[PDB]
């Protein structure tokens, strides 16, 4: 009966499991309840702290995945199934996981806290690609990851109402961060050295905790991978949030009091809400999600973009970056002429049609400005160039330029910023070659998944993964990824970043500076007049 | 006695010319042929009336007066500016034309080249040294004609709808000269069935307007547009703005002491010509470069619609045109008002001066339009580099006013049935007096087209004399056949391939795109922005 796997937290006693890695054992505590189950009357409500328990909670296996849409675009395809739930769906899903070295550390060790992505409509801390055992063994850190409510269950908002205030999925994350502050020392973690990191909507979540004062005291450093809180998909206004919530109620046979409305929604099975989730969007689109954080003055006192411009970020260190081809993944989900199973050599007409889908809810004039900038007017109809251009449109608008704006504003306002572009295409990648390095496929290297012997990564890849784990952990420990070729900080003027691939670090200038000047500087002025 | 080669009878009466010496042999020149009644006194602002017949022999032996115009004083005594200033006395009695013909007179009908000078519709003269037609005629055996036309208020002041000052009379001066060519050029040996118009800057815009005006279209067969287009943002003005500028000029000179148009023009006609010139520039609505007070007006008569509309909607089958630009169209105009610019220093401007220059180089556009210009012409990896900013503002002014209007005209004509040839002139003359940073400025291909390097009193290199002879051959080949190529090839310009040739001391090099990325902004996007 192993004392290393027995831990007492404030709520009671836990029993963990000893996990094997190629580098030696790891202690894991999986499925720790940090909130009361948000069931029945608690649906749509802020999380409530988990009440204490007697006896020993079995923390030896992942708990349920929060209720979410399950992707069916390519059934059985590894490229999509790796993101789908690998545990049963349940609204009883507010659990977190702790990985720690074996034996448990006696002195405080820096803590890494992972927030998964998935467009605020999906995701789980139990996915194979988020396995924390390799990072913990290799870099001697404590790693924490939590489940948080997604879709309507986490972000349906009737603003001003108590029954459905919105942003409760963000409050799930905050409660887990508060849990870390109060309990991580029992596992050997240092609550005074907590580094948030997340990808896609998880990166947008990290940025929103940066911009919400009640969350700012719960961590010390931040890593934003391929996502930003100022992304055009990451927040929604109060009026549009109310419209989407009201439209969902109509679609599921629900009725006008906000109270009556939510009460009827609470009688519906969770799967029924999921089945109508995508139908409340105003337009046919890619890279848009129905229920996302709402700007209502509470969690976010203003839009993330306003909060970024007006903040004093002295004393903050951030690590941000993007993959080489942020836009390609999303094109197969609705852009005309695109598929993972052919070359997606689109025509000019399909390109123009894709622009309206990839840049939804903008005026015709705004769309024409997009076409002007992303057309090569010496080769206006070349299919290969059009395919690459539409990928750039979607990737720049939704990921690269929001990340570039956040990096530049934080750096100019006192933060130390390190920026990267991930440019290695995994030898095991199942997506076609034309997609390049797609969104989300740096994660497996950050987590050291290539070190798993049962996988088919090359020897060079394993060394690459170990390099990236060292950068990320160096940043967690010191706020500086460099090993004491150097990685210089990103600044609004020099705009320096490094490329991450099998070659040594290469310093370059500009995160798509010409393109992002369009999205970040001109287009806001066009839309306002 | 008399040299029969220098005696010609036209419809108005008899003329006596002069024999000119050229390095290649003699040429007959008839300079100062009256083609209209002098538009003086009551005839000021009125359409030209044909010159009434005369008895005896008119001596057409020297250039006549320059039409009344502003005289540039930016760099007094400087060759780069003085070469464009009048070289004859100013007078409203200025409606004369010139004919150069080979000596002896041609035996069979010879193709005719007709030159229309530029000068922003406010200046210019057919008598400038750089327009000397003796070298083209001797080298290529063509007949060359050039005319004076009224400029400034005298040629383009418009009170639209008014009978006393209808506007566009300077264009009617050009048309009357073209009608004179049809009726009389055969007496000099010229072929009235093979007439090629060519002009530069506002002369090129004038050529394009004759292409788009049916009464002029029957008077010529081919066109050459050098560094100018009728669809340039400076080349035409609306009816209301023309009336506002004309009314403001009258107000500035004490007329009336608006109101009745007849009375208004009658008061203007009592003012000395120099008094009108002295107030010409004060009627512009905004501080700017590349904008001129009195230009052709779109009033439904000479131009039934805007040139852009007429170009987009026209059928141009059976037409051959040659168009082109110099390498640095914008640089010349920057020293005339862009902050931080001068011919006497490097003009390495700051970011603030660049932003200020954009409003001067793109006048009368909304703040949003100006922001679009700044977005496009800023290198956001080097947003404050002075050298890059200087080059960028030159591109802004050159693309907006010359390159992109020419590219739009070239693309639409080619797509709608015309045979188009396009060039970029990239040779900086060894004799150029402008600073090195200005590159190949606007207007400095003309001396090579006219073969000026062949003048023995000039100091051009031997390569430049060979170069000049190449260009004269291209232009005359086009005049004779509609194809500059010899009976390295010059391919036609098309809306898709967008092929043009570089003209310099090296052989022809074929390239693609007349600043396609930049001109997509000016020609395709910016119009949509201004309408919303
Ligand atoms: C590339 O594929 C897309 C997607 O089509 C699907 O996948 C293909 C592998 C094939 O099995 C198709 O039959 C599938 O529908 C093609 O775009 C579709 O084209 C059809 C016309 O044949 C049209 O009815 C659909 O609406 C199109 N779908 C989308 C999303 O645009 C595309 O034509 C293929 N490119 C080729 C073949 O060059
Ligand atoms: C605008 O004024 C003209 C000119 O009026 C003439 O000149 C003034 C100085 C004054 O002496 C008037 O008495 C003159 O008549 C008008 O054109 C004249 O119209 C009359 C009547 O139809 C005619 O007999 C004259 O020949 C015209 N003179 C011309 C054409 O030179 C014109 O009608 C006025 N328009 C208005 C007031 O709208
Ligand atoms: C480059 O020259 C301009 C023009 O100034 C004139 O020309 C210069 C060559 C020199 O002879 C000056 O004395 C002339 O006044 C400079 O811009 C001017 O700067 C002065 C004061 O420095 C100001 O009063 C004028 O308004 C400016 N004019 C314009 C059009 O901006 C410019 O500063 C010079 N650049 C240098 C020296 O780097
Ligand atoms: P992100 O939330 N993340 C996505 C789509 N992902 C699958 C590749 C990683 C979990 O994108 C929407 C912002
Ligand atoms: C539209 C303004 O440009 P154009 O009229 N021509 C110019 C300025 N010159 C002087 C270099 C040639 C006569």
Image (tube, coloured by chain):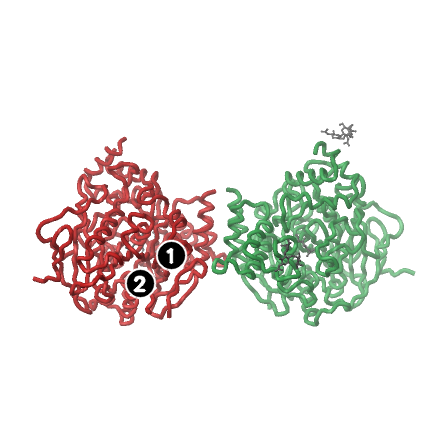
Chain colours: A red, B green
Q: Which residue is mark 2?
A: A478
Measured in 3D between alpha carbons, the distance from the residue under mark 1 to the one under mark 2, in whole angstroms, is 14 Å
Q: Chain of mark 2?
A: A
Residue B262's image quarter?
top right
Q: Is residue B54 among the parts visible in the rendering? A: yes
Q: Chain of mark 1?
A: A
Residue found at x 78% / y 59%: B100
Location of residue A34 in the rendering, given as x and y in whole percent from the top left corner: 18, 50
Location of residue A478 in the rendering, given as x and y in whole percent from the top left corner: 31, 63
Q: Is residue B8 above or below residue A277?
A: below
Q: Nearer the viewer, residue B277 or B77?
A: B77
- Image quarter where the N terminus of chain B lies is bottom right
Q: Is residue B411 above or below residue A262?
A: below
Which dot marks residue A470? Answer: none
Q: How many numbered circles does the render carry? A: 2
Residue found at x 7% / y 62%: A1
Check disc 1 and report its element: helix, strand or loop.
loop
Which residue is at the far left?
Answer: A1
Q: Is residue A45 left or right of residue B44?
A: left
Check disc 2 and report its element: helix, strand or loop.
helix
Residue B243's image quarter?
top right
The answer to which of marks 1 and 2 sits earlier in the sequence is 1
Q: Is residue B528 among the parts visible in the rendering? A: no
Whether the residues at callouts 1 and 2 have beta carbons within 8 Å, the answer is no
Q: Which residue is mark 1?
A: A415
Location of residue A312 in the rendering, given as x and y in whole percent from the top left corner: 38, 51
Q: Is residue A400 left or right of residue B303?
A: left
Which corner quadrant of the figure contains ligand 2? Answer: top right
Residue found at x 44% / y 44%: A363
Task: Categorize mark 2 by other alpha carbons within 10 Å: few (<14), some (14-19), many (20+).
Answer: few
Q: Nearer the viewer, residue A290 or B178?
A: A290
**Is label 2's Cβ within 8 Å of ligand 4?**
no
């Amino acid at each position: 009966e192993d004392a290393e796997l027995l831990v007492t937290v404030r709520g009671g006693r836990l029993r963990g499991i000893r996990l094997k890695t190629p580098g030696g054992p790891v202690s894991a505590f999986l499925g720790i309840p940090f909130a009361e189950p948000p069931m029945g009357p608690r649906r749509f409500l802020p999380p409530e702290p988990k009440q204490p328990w007697s006896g020993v909670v079995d923390a030896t296996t992942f708990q349920s995945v929060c209720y979410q849409y399950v992707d069916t675009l390519y059934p059985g395809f590894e490229g999509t199934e790796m993101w789908n739930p690998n545990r049963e769906l349940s609204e009883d899903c507010l659990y977190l996981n702790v990985w720690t070295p074996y034996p448990r550390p006696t002195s405080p060790t820096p803590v890494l806290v992972w927030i998964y992505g998935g467009g605020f409509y999906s995701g789980a801390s139990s996915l194979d690609v988020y396995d924390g055992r390799f990072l913990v063994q290799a870099e001697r850190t404590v790693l924490v990851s939590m489940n948080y409510r997604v879709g309507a269950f986490g972000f349906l908002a009737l603003p001003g109402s108590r029954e459905a205030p919105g942003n409760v999925g963000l409050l799930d994350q905050r409660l887990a961060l508060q849990w870390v502050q109060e309990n991580v020392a029992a596992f050997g973690g240092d609550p005074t050295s907590v580094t948030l990191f997340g990808e896609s909507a998880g990166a947008a979540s990290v940025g929103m905790h940066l911009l919400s004062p009640p969350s700012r005291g719960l961590f010390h450093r931040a890593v934003l991978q391929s996502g930003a809180p100022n992304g055009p998909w990451a927040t929604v206004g109060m009026g549009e949030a109310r419209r989407r919530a009201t439209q969902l109620a109509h679609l599921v046979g629900c009725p006008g009091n906000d109270t009556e409305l939510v009460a009827c929604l609470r009688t519906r099975p969770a799967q029924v809400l999921v089945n109508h989730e995508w139908h409340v969007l105003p337009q046919e689109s890619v890279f848009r999600f129905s229920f996302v954080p709402v700007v209502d003055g509470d969690f976010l006192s203003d839009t993330p973009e306003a909060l970024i411009n007006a903040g004093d970020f002295h004393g903050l260190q951030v690590l941000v970056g993007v993959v080489k081809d942020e836009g390609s993944y999303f094109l197969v989900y609705g852009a005309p002429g695109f598929s993972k199973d052919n070359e997606s050599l689109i025509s000019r007409a399909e390109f123009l049609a894709g622009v309206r889908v990839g840049v939804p809810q903008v005026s015709d004039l705004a769309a024409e400005a997009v076409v002007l900038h992303y057309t090569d007017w010496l080769h206006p109809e070349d299919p290969a160039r059009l395919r690459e251009a539409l990928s750039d449109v979607v990737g720049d608008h939704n990921v690269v330029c929001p990340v570039a704006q956040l990096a530049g504003r934080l750096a100019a306002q006192g933060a130390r910023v390190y920026a990267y572009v991930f440019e290695h295409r995994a030898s095991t990648l199942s997506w076609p070659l034309w997609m390049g390095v797609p969104h989300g496929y740096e994660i497996e290297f950050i987590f050291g998944i290539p070190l798993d012997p049962s996988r088919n990564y090359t020897a060079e890849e394993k060394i690459f993964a170990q390099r990236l784990m060292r950068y990320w952990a160096n940043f967690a420990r010191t706020g500086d990824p460099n090993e004491p070729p150097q990685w210089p900080p990103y600044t609004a003027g020099a705009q320096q970043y490094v490329s991450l691939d099998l070659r040594p670090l290469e310093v370059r200038r500009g995160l798509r500076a010409q393109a992002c000047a369009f999205w970040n500087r001109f287009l806001p002025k066009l839309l306002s007049a």
